[PDB]
Image (cartoon, rainbow over all chains, first blue to last red; front, top):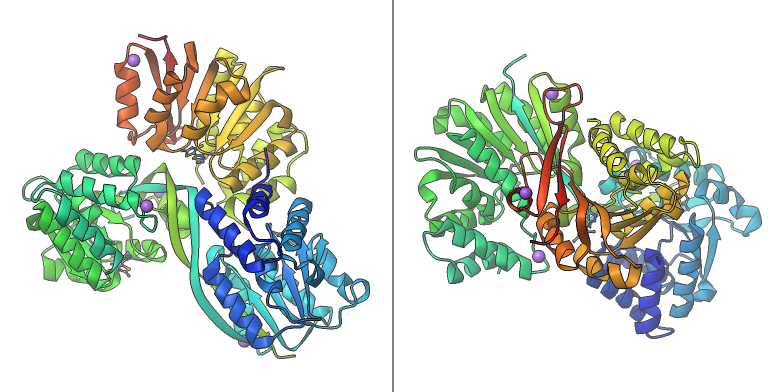
Length: 215
Length: 213
Length: 212
Ligand SMILES: Cc1nc(C)c(-c2cc(CN)[nH]n2)s1
Ligand SMILES: Cc1nc(C)c(-c2cc(CN)[nH]n2)s1
Ligand SMILES: Cc1nc(C)c(-c2cc(CN)[nH]n2)s1
Ligand code: NA
Ligand code: NA
Ligand code: NA
Ligand code: NA
Ligand code: NA
């Protein structure tokens, strides 16, 4: 059977307008709605991401986690000429799909896709990919890695004063260590944008509990 | 209008006044159409029905009313003399629930309390003449299942044999509540699996701007 | 990062590759950390049913994280197929990875979609005559409709075993009334208590007797 990401890409290729990032994003949205698949990042979170990018005009963005490439298209389409997105993806098939999604969108020249784990690639950014400091980091990979990778980014000298970290899913499934750390630290000035997450077609459950009397 | 007011209007325009089954079927029909709407679970409703028929509670506490589907579904199975108390924090939802019960003809069995569970629970004995509760349906804010259960205990509102039924203990999940009642010798627990077509929860994005050391 | 995706990461970092037993034990270990041993309660019944009937073609409705697929596939005789329907695409992907790590991928075909869409395609698209066993473990609202649909499509024969999971209260009274009331099914109920006084899991076995 075809992967979830392959099917999304195929719908884009058959329905979106080539070279039109907005058309690509709408076709992903339309397909996920039709299939009743929950979106990793939809338009609600996407509008928050757009607003941050437009406010800070980052020239170099690091993205942790690519999925089918929706978020990469969402951010890359707003980058100025000369600006650059680096996307880390641990799954080689998602990395290939993201590359092909960006190609269809006409955004291939703005994005470099790195296949591997964040903690293996981050220490290579300076020498292997000629990075000085990052202007913005979008964290959307394994939730238990947000704080370690933030500390790793700091230890590697990849953060400058004014680097924007934008972290998805900090409430659900949640990154409570990351939040407590950056909010408590004087090294980070923190703003939280409330939104929503959707679940579709998941196992749930009920509990019956019969009180036995005080014990 | 609000999404719950539209469900109420659909009931009032299509269901038979005085017929709880008709009201329940109309809500089900309307929610299935509307893609924004939480669908009603068949097996979940049957679990609720079976729990009420098995224990025949004379006094039920419901935490979280929403639009009144569950209040109609439970109150329709209460024996004469039994009552349901429903706590709902949203005033428009409390009003719609009252109108749903009025249309179903069930309003004499139910008392709707508009407010927060941890404010209202301590008032039950003195203000609403409660001795102990026979059954509690937990369906409100998931992070409140555990503290409100502990509060129901502390207030002396549970007796031996009181049945707690908690929904959504896996998604979004109430792991601390489950750890408590399963690990406590004060509760005998049974788990029922279920399936959710759709659920929307609060999430957020954090913007953290590095300042330097 | 999802609740099921972390089970897969825990298996990958703890179980022995190609060994279905250690994969099951890794999942059982993981799920018991955070509490009831449903894997054992449910899996003990599944094992006994599979070993009694030695099915050559099993249809599994619902996969979740792949535990049940690894559980049944590890017991299948050489040349036996498991077809697994899972509507959630993330759970389908996890189950495939779970089966890959256990070394059972060649016994199983994962179909990602809804049972009412997929069941009518089994004969044409997946070269199915009739099924030897069906494991109902998906949406309880679909237990009865899919049982009727499997009949209508001609996918059951005399002796086909249906086994329905988590029938306790029951939340599926219409399904039970149908198979128990019908002379076309001989029925057995299993209640697993493990060492406790409450039912950890309950299952209905319904054996098709033929059209009537
Ligand atoms: C340690 C990790 N590094 C990366 C890039 C990860 C990741 C997570 C996802 C989403 N499935 N894509 N990439 S996890
Ligand atoms: C602290 C709270 N008390 C109550 C009654 C709450 C509630 C939750 C819902 C469902 N949205 N209705 N009422 S939250
Ligand atoms: C109509 C449906 N078809 C299928 C395969 C469903 C399902 C439910 C679950 C829960 N694990 N998995 N697949 S619902
Ligand atoms: Na995300
Ligand atoms: Na701070
Ligand atoms: Na709906
Ligand atoms: Na207990
Ligand atoms: Na029968």
